[PDB]
Image (cartoon, coloured by chain):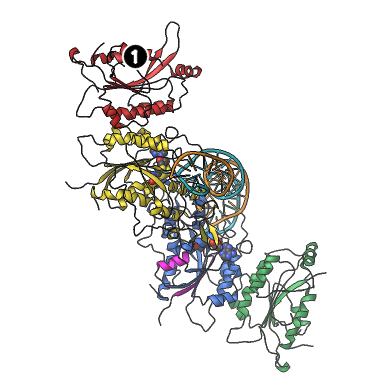
Chain colours: A red, B yellow, C blue, D green, E orange, F cyan
DNA sequence: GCATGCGTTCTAATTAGAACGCATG
DNA sequence: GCATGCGTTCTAATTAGAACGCATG
């Protein structure tokens, strides 16, 4: 959904739930998170197989849910789709009830770890095509992610598909977080 | 205040056991939307129910809007393919690969069909799969459906072994299973004239013919005119509880019909599970 | 002056059409002795008539004493194989070699079963074969049966061409053939749900599949869901006038069932021929 | 199929019906027919395809019906079974009715022109095994009460090749105890 | 004129029948 | 418990489908 901007004085510190990957030290850099709170507003968890709704409900409320694949490599024990389906599972636990519509956002990013069949189920489950964020500069290093998100932030797959053969990039995810300054406190 | 006919979404419909059981219970069926991929299963449902079933093809192409327009639904049922979940196959690509991941399509559409919270409307659903799966798969499935399964073996009400897991929220799923007056509990009770059953109960019938000859001995289950024989398609229909000749369709032979029947539900088990629905919907 | 049930000798019985027609007419059948060698034909007659038919195997092993012991007979019927009598086969062997000479076995047993002179008791018989034979064979057959044949084409009472010769002494064999209320005269009348017939009548059905698609064009006779299709076993049973699923026996598939149906009699033609027998024998 | 002997004074000239082969000049040698009257007691016919019962009945009563295959060294005009079935056809026309039992006999002979399963059709239709009377041989089916070689011998005898009337006639004699003897 | 058909015979498809398998219960 | 089973793969056949055919009319 579209959410109206907050007046600056009513903005609050985000409560976020980040699965598989931790964006804690990242998100502090943009001031969404504050280094004073020992009980951080970020909850991180990696083995989510035995997480129940009642776990998510008392670890929250949350305003942002973030999930990500392991980086390209890592010797992944789990099938790459597993990170998708589990992220989709909890995200439903964390959504606000219909009768309490608050600003609420979610992001999922993949490290080129998902095949084409997995990406087509990724976009059926998250109800949108991904957007391809590339890394390349004056030395022309090669690195990429694709993101699914309801955040208003938002190339050839020849290049991507042969890139993958030869081998976490926060650099590319971080810029999509800053349209959330219009909803939560800044620094 | 009155009751209206039931509106059903049936994923992986197979040979329309869901519809058959409902019509056999006297429940008025207002809409039956079935997603199914195999052409000869579809022919069976089409011909045997004269076009009452609305077929919509691949479950993975049903959209959130589809669920809005085809619905509302009162009952969402499904039984996903077990090629990659059963330990019967050495090659199992698990819950997350191959066809095992079609389960999540059921989980996905189930959520689309669920009423919103303001709606305290009646809503029932049920998901079935085999028992011969990994404990991790069984754990994750009921992580996603948020409930645990009942095990019901058709041997209590059928002439064959068939142990299955059923998740859902139907009334009384956990109650004891009792045979009814017209259940054919022994193999003899399902054979044609002039055929002798060697056993009273038969091992689990799968899609391949080696499931019909019994145990370590691999013995033919029937004697006719003194020589042993395998089971006939009408006798398979009878064991599973289908009407005789239910699969006598589309020029299918022994193999095709055993495939459809071997992956089917046991009609008397589904009848047991669906029977408490009579008090929530219209009846003829 | 009372009537008793009819006692029948049926040579080359096939799928027991003779018995089926008699039971459909309400005639009490006291004994039905059938000579037949094909195992799947025998399975059909056995299962579909619950053991009322006494099978006696190869016609050439029936003895004069057999006819004495199994009889007396009121009705002797038969239709011998036409592999060597038809023009449809290039390698005809004719009436005197191959299987064409099985006709004389019928001629032979007919004479054993006939009542002796002085016995004015009712005795009826009928022999059928195809029209596509040469005049020499047709002449010799009716030299041996001492009478000439009626030609009856099932196109008048069924959805298919099939012209056959009938010799015999039944009452009224030469009368005109009229359709009854429940004769399915057009191909559409015999198809399953959601299938379209392209023709109203189909060319003569043989045991081989190439007789199902019509004419020079060799066009599939049915349209289903927009695509062309051949006929189904149930649709063949309806064309020939058999009960639906009559041949759904012994795991037979499309080929097996078409073989049995393709060489069988058209039920409504036999009903027409057998109907005058109601006034000579006991009735249900 | 068995008849009491008749006294000699009441014996009468036999009436015979011989099909395919003619035994007329044959049978007169044994005095069954009297060489004299052209309208004999023996009726001969070869092409029986269009003969009806009414033909056989108006050809007058018969006491003996005889049929035989063509000789071996001969053109197979018709299938060898044809002579069998046709012989069986008219023999039934010629039999006396049940209510008129009169000595009545029949004979069928083959020139080794019939294969094995043809012979099994022969003996089920004529209700008896044949007797093989023998280098050359024939086998007869007959109800007249007159009636040592491997069929290996006979079957390889047959291949390398004239009706052998020589051999059939001696089985005809026991009919002298029913019909007149001409000297 | 020349269209049809109670089929036998080729080959190319489907199909049928056993081994193969180990967690789950 | 030490056997069981909503199956895939191999091969051995089963079977399917199209030319082939000419007298009966
Ligand atoms: N992608 C898909 N979309 C819809 N149906 C599918 C599918 N993939 C497989 N199927 C079907 O799902 C079924 C699973 S077996 C279920 C049979 C059914 N419960 C019955 O009672 O008969 C099979 O019929 C299979 O053909
Ligand atoms: N030697 C024999 N003895 C008895 N039956 C035989 C036979 N040889 C062939 N047959 C059978 O004769 C039948 C001729 S087809 C006749 C079918 C029958 N008119 C019906 O209505 O179904 C075939 O079933 C064939 O199996």
Q: What x and y, as percent, mark residue B110?
A: 31, 36
Q: What x and y, as percent, mark residue C135?
A: 57, 63
Q: Is residue C16 magenta?
A: yes
Quadrant where the C terminus of chain C sits is bottom left
**Which is more toward the observer, C45 or A28?**
A28
Q: What residue range appears in magenta?
A: C4-28
Please identify the quarter of the rendering in which residue B97 is found: top left
Q: Residues within 10 Å of mark 1 (few under 14, many from 20)?
A: some
Quadrant where the N terminus of chain C sits is bottom left
Q: Is residue B32 above or below residue D97?
A: above
Q: Chain of mark 1?
A: A
**Which is more toward the observer, A130 or C229?**
A130
Which residue is at a point 64% across and 62% down the rendered structure image? C97
**Which is more toward the observer, B40 or E23?**
E23
The answer to whether residue C175 is visible is no
Please identify the quarter of the rendering in which residue C68 is found: bottom right
In the rendered view, does A119 fall on the left or right side of D162? left
Please identify the quarter of the rendering in which residue A28 is found: top left
Q: Which residue is mark 1?
A: A26
Which residue is at a point 28% across and 27% down the rendered structure image? A94
- Disc 1, ligand 1: is the CB inside 8 Å? no
In the rendered view, does B240 fall on the left or right side of C166? left
Q: Is residue C121 magenta?
A: no
Q: What x and y, as percent, mark residue B85?
A: 44, 38
Q: What x and y, as percent, mark residue D125?
A: 64, 73
Q: Is residue D175 above or below residue C31?
A: below
Q: Is residue D97 above or below residue B109?
A: below
The answer to whether residue B178 is visible is yes
């Amino acid at each position: 959904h579209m959410f109206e901007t907050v007046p600056v004085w009513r903005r609050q510190p985000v409560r976020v739930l980040s699965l598989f990957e931790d964006i804690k030290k990242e998100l502090t850099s943009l001031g969404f998170l504050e280094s004073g709170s020992d009980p951080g507003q970020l909850k991180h968890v990696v083995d989510v197989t035995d997480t129940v709704r009642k776990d998510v409900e008392e670890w929250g409320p949350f305003d942002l849910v973030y999930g990500a694949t392991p980086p390209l490599g890592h010797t992944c024990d789990r099938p790459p789709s597993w990170y998708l389906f589990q992220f989709h599972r909890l995200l439903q636990y964390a959504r606000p009830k219909p009768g309490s519509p608050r600003p609420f956002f979610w992001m999922f990013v993949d490290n080129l770890v998902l095949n084409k069949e997995d990406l087509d189920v990724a976009s059926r489950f998250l109800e949108m095509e991904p957007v391809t964020i590339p890394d390349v500069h004056g030395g022309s290093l090669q690195n990429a992610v694709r993101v699914w998100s309801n955040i208003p932030a938002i190339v050839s797959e020849e290049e991507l598909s042969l890139l993958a053969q030869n081998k976490w990039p926060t650099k590319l995810v971080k810029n999509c977080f800053l349209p959330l300054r219009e909803y939560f406190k800044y620094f | 205040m009155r009751r209206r006919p039931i509106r059903v979404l049936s994923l992986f419909d197979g040979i329309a056991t869901g519809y058959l059981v409902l019509k056999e219970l006297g429940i008025k069926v207002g809409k039956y939307v079935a997603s199914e991929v195999c052409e000869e299963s579809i022919a069976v449902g089409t011909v045997k129910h004269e076009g009452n079933i609305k077929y919509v093809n691949d479950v993975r192409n049903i959209t959130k809007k589809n669920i809005e327009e085809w619905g509302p639904f009162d009952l969402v049922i499904g039984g996903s393919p077990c090629n990659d979940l059963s330990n019967v196959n050495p090659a199992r690509k698990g819950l997350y690969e191959g066809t095992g991941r079609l389960f999540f399509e059921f989980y996905h559409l189930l959520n689309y069909s669920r009423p919103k919270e303001g709606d305290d409307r009646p809503f029932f659903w049920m998901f079935e799969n085999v028992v011969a799966m990994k404990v991790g798969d069984k754990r994750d499935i009921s992580r996603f459906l948020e409930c645990n399964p009942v095990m019901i073996d058709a041997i209590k009400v059928s002439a064959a072994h068939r142990a299955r897991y059923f998740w859902g929220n139907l009334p009384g799923m956990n109650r004891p299973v009792i045979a009814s007056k017209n259940d054919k509990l022994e193999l003899q009770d399902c054979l044609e004239y002039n055929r002798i059953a060697k056993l009273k109960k038969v091992q689990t019938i799968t899609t391949k013919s080696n499931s019909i000859k019994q145990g370590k001995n691999q013995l033919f289950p029937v004697v006719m005119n003194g020589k042993e024989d395998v089971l006939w398609c009408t006798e398979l229909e009878r064991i599973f509880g289908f009407p005789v000749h239910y699969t006598d369709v589309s020029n299918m032979g022994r193999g095709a019909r055993q495939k459809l029947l071997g992956r089917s539900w046991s009609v008397p088990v589904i009848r047991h599970l669906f029977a408490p629905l009579k008090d929530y919907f219209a009846c003829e």
